[PDB]
Length: 136
Length: 6
Ligand SMILES: [Zn+2]
Image 1 (cartoon, helix red, strand yellow):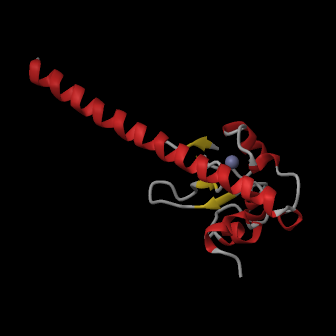
Image 2: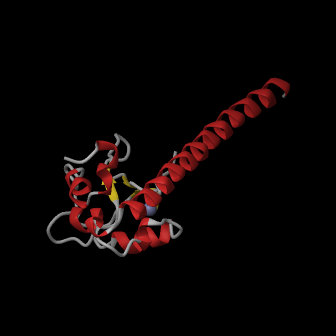
């Protein structure tokens, strides 16, 4: 088998992650077509159709059956490197693969930072509002 | 689709 951390590089693992994905047979954003685009299904309560690139970590809710997940990926995250991987996985080299994984680990960190930032600006707003009300 | 919010 393949080291679990490295698993989302696998189209078939990514597919397997779609569990009760609403858009099946007749749709353009089918789990197959979705995994092919690098998404994994990571549903929440308020967001049951939440999908995420395993590589750039962009997150997209609000899918419509006519959406082409590739086109939708170039749109909301053109910078993503997986988008450029022409080759099929096992056609890669370990060298090429490790380059890619390093970039993933970097994008992940980049994403963590980015969230911590929003969390920070959220807390700020609360503090601002409070102080204002307290001065009023 | 949309970029996630909140
Ligand atoms: Zn991506």
